[PDB]
Image (cartoon, rainbow, N blue to C red):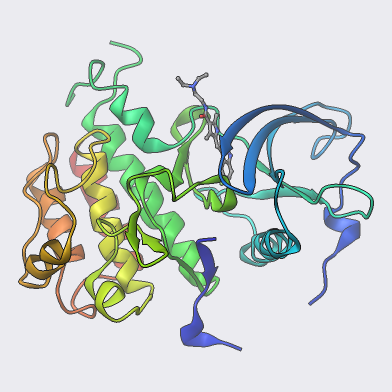
Length: 303
Ligand SMILES: CCN(CC)CCNC(=O)c1c(C)[nH]c(/C=C2\C(=O)Nc3ccc(F)cc32)c1C
């Protein structure tokens, strides 16, 4: 799984009174995403936060063929979920069924519109830079800004997202977007955004260079990812580096300071933003804390 704590800053038990939730107050439904051993299922959960009100949630759980190895992975996600705590632009934990005699289940915010990529890619027809339902440039700046913030909070809690992409970002009601980690519920052996490298399969289009050549994950080799994330947005859900075969070659030109062109809906400011994020030197490219403001700036400038 992908959202983990920053190793740049290592080196507390589970609070059941605050988190544990009755498997008999939880009603399972359709799968939203299946991966290999994991799956996110849509659920209805009674009085999980408002006494006596039902509530549509998303429950993370194992599926068939998982081993205790997975189960421990899922015990981990809950743990860091509890760590990071509530922010609005990230997915939040609602509660957990960690009782014996039952499947481990982590319950998290449901997002009615799913991941951003597939959402924008569907909105290509209904867009305009400046009529209800339609996407505008105001929205696009806004989403970007929300993720920066989300990424910032995600930093403040000493975490890193080792797979930051528009496909791991969800849209819910009222134009809120939340950073998430599909974790086990994403199969990388079946998603082409993930390239085989040995038996490791990596989101290479998103991965910053230092991460690729060496394997240095940092809040900053994330900004790069976020630069790429910005592209996906102002292309309305287009996959990065079109046509370009991702190979020993690709990686080369990348550190020759070679970047993608501009996406179809980008503004000039946005594109240059994307270009900072894609600095060779991981230090030169801004902090998410700094992107939060520029985008805040840009969002005011778009009326
Ligand atoms: C044609 C479009 N479809 C209509 C039937 C839309 C389908 N909807 C979907 O695919 C979908 C929806 C509505 N939610 C999710 C995922 C998550 C969610 O909600 N909270 C999370 C929290 C954490 C996490 F790691 C994933 C999720 C999907 C994949």
